[PDB]
Image: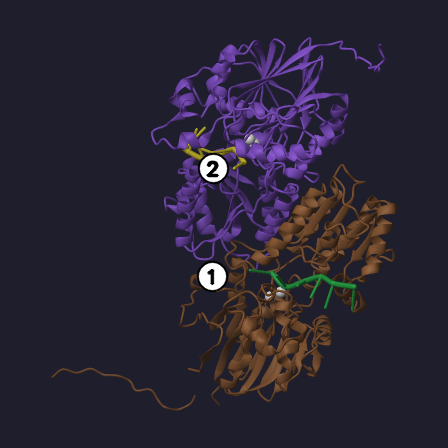
Chain colours: A purple, B brown, C green, D yellow
Amino acid sequence: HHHSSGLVPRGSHMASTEIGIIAVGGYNEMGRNMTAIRVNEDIIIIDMGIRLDRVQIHEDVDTDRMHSLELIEMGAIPDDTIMNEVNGNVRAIVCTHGHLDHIGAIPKLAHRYAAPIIATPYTTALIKHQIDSERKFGVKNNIVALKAGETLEITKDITIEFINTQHSIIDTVFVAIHTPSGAVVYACDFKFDRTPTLGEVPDFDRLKELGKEGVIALITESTNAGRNGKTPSELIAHMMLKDVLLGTEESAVGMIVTTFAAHIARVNSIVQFAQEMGRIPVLLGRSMERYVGTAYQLGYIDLPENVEIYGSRRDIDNALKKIMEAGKDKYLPVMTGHQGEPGAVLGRIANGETPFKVETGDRIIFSANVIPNPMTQANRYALETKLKMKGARIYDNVHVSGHAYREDHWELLRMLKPEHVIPAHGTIQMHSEYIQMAEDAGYSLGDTLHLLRNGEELYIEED
Amino acid sequence: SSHHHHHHSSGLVPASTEIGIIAVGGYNEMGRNMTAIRVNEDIIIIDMGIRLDRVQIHEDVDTDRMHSLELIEMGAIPDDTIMNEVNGNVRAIVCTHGHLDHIGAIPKLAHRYAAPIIATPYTTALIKHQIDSERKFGVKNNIVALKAGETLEITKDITIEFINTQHSIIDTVFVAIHTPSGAVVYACDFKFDRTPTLGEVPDFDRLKELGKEGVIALITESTNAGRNGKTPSELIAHMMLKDVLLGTEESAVGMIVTTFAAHIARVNSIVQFAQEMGRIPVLLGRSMERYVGTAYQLGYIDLPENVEIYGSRRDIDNALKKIMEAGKDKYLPVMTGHQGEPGAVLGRIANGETPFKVETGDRIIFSANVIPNPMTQANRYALETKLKMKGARIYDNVHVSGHAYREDHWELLRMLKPEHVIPAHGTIQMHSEYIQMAEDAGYSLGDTLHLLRNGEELYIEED
RNA sequence: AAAAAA
RNA sequence: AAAAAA
Ligand SMILES: [Zn+2]
Ligand SMILES: [Zn+2]
Ligand SMILES: [Zn+2]
Ligand SMILES: [Zn+2]
């Protein structure tokens, strides 16, 4: 009557953890990133960012005076009101680095959470400055510096680990949240760089170790997952910049370099080249003085003792007057204004509001890309037109990306071996590209590969 | 009553040379370049090239068997019949380098001119091979090897000087035709590279000397004059390739590199990297063997004694079978097929017509660009689809251009100080970009800056 | 941005 | 691909 069919060994389940991946902002767009990681009833927030272009489309703005609710209505700050309906209490806010798409919304949203703000030293300095620049939301959260390779136990069941990585700003980290059932890894704004000009090479060994210890979920940026191959190293930008600055038959012509003030590796390269060219490096711009000086006071960069740094309008105008009468061949001005921002040094120069006069053949080196949005594109077009009309020669895009490419994401999937993968930090189109890469690696959409929209919670019941 | 005055000039001399710039091919399109420089009745032809896409659009066509007139009707070679209306006798044919857009039409057009063919040693080797495979015209011009930095006296009034430059193939030169009234400089397919991995740095000193001695006219390529800034050095391609090949956590996976067979510097880099990776470099492909062997056999490269080189179908299939049974992680195959050419090694592999089987995770590195015309785009798309469907990971465009950018052209204008400038070697759109740069430098179109079409002769007289 | 092809 | 603004 009855035949035996077979046997199956049932596994043990010694620890049941309910994980929640909550997408607050930056899953439908570039900017205003915010993620919440729930471990049963505790919540770790990662990255309260701003979306700058939605600010730029309104002329009468002054983000500093606006309340967070209007900023949410504008879509510039993550709509974190969904947090009142996530089942848990926030125990920490973590920021992976100091870019505004990760810390820009801190002074508008952090004060409502009874939780510290945990970040790397440079990031904590930048967060403190960002909060100090507003006196409308009095945000006085405890601010904790956690260095890369260090751990901090936030709950008996939750620990936070920073992993060193590379990016277009120093002191970027992966975040690993360790839970009774494994690790949740957050990797947004990262880049593998085996030859960085500043810092150490990302911790591939620890990444393999984490992959072997158990990763429940990987939250990772999708920004350049559609660019084939691997990201070029910062060394490539360094060498291209060296060739533009030194490899020329027009040594004694005027030269200006503009780049991101927070791109400390790039700025460091530029000032060392200045020493090679026999020119004095002159950093111009409030943001230049702030960011480079902060880096210097934390021991992140070294600086030649002939460097000159001016952030004040009249010190800047005076330095430019001194440069003009001493000879532009005698200095290398590194200044703000690469996106044509009004009020930045290069834009005031282009408008003739300056003692510095651009002449035919003067070289202007944009060690940056143009941010692909119509607003910044219009500003850069106006600035470049003005500079070209005064005879300047433009060296654009002397630059490499700060984001992992498709094959970098492939390698990170192979190292971390996550049970689940969640693309973050982009549009649904960038997520599409990531999804096709992840399917190539074995993941399945809606099963182990998850497409989230702003305001959605993915629940993971890990045995 | 009314009165004024004027000084009449003397009709006396304080012996007249007429210069002619004749555009035959390559001024309306990419490919089939050919220029004629006339000094009163003597003519120096520069570059009889082929335009390959006009061949590719016709099904199953044997250019080697075709007459010159059918090829001209196809648009695939310069229409030199206009030479029967130019008042002079051709005294020399000069080729600036061995690319097919400069030498491909030689076995169809050179034999009708009572003149030698003058080129650099490597270029002469390639020309001799090109003639040997010709099967319709009996070509018996003498081929004279002239090294860079040497001069050769062609007529009582005309000498030819080669100046070394950098390009995507070794032994490229500028040509300076010295006449009684000054020099005519031809600079097509050149690139400034202060750190080349092969050859010497272009002779900037001689270029300045020429500019000060007197240059009547500069004929120059416009190919990338619309690219802002300066061309990245070949060292950049070298370092990107080094990082792709060496910078990975997947040491023991299969890797295949494809690149231009004539890019001897790139191939040299790849083989030295193979030595670093602990793999055996195996060059596969008829063109690979021909070009690399000619370079090695003339002392342009050195090669490790473990290198293997196979141009024959069965040596190739045997080497691939040996690679599969010895382990793909133990070899670095450098092969033809980067444009998806049918019959090339990579294409036959993708078609599964070889012992080599591509598996998931195998890396295919195109150290090349996709040539922007619909035919090669279709071929590369088919090849890439086939490779991706077999699990390959694609690293594309690990590559830098071999052509000067806008500011490189600016500095060459500043060095050579030509009286007249003539853009060549591109479409009228590329010439538009050049013209806009040259107007920035003081030239005026139709006066000292001249946009010529195929089949036009520009006259340059003495004041 | 000018091949591949034995 | 996330600013500037003494
Ligand atoms: Zn960032
Ligand atoms: Zn970001
Ligand atoms: Zn060429
Ligand atoms: Zn060419």
Q: Quadrant of residue A64?
A: top left
Secondary element under disc 2, as helix, strand or loop, is loop
Q: CA distance from mark 2 to mark 1?
A: 39 Å
Q: Is residue A210 visible?
A: yes
Amino acid carrying label 1: it is Gln
Element at label 1? helix
What chain letter is assigned to the residue under label 1? B
Density class for disc 1 (Cα within 10 Å; few <14, some 14-19, many ≥20) is some
Same chain under badges 2 and 1? The reply is: no
Circle 2 is placed at which residue position?
Answer: A285
Q: Residue furthest front?
A: A1
Q: Which residue is mark 1?
A: B429
Front residue of B57/B320: it is B57
Q: Position of residue B199 (x, y in %)?
A: 71, 63
Residue at horizontal 42 percent and vertical 63 percent from the top = B439
Which image quarter is the C terminus of chain A in?
Answer: top right
Give the image location of residue A171, x and y in percent.
63, 29
Q: Is residue A417 above or below residue B412?
A: above
Indicate which quadrant contains ligand 1. top right
B454 or B19, which is in the foreground? B454
**On-image quarter of the N terminus of chain A:** top right
Q: Identify which residue, B261 or A314, lies in the foreground.
A: B261
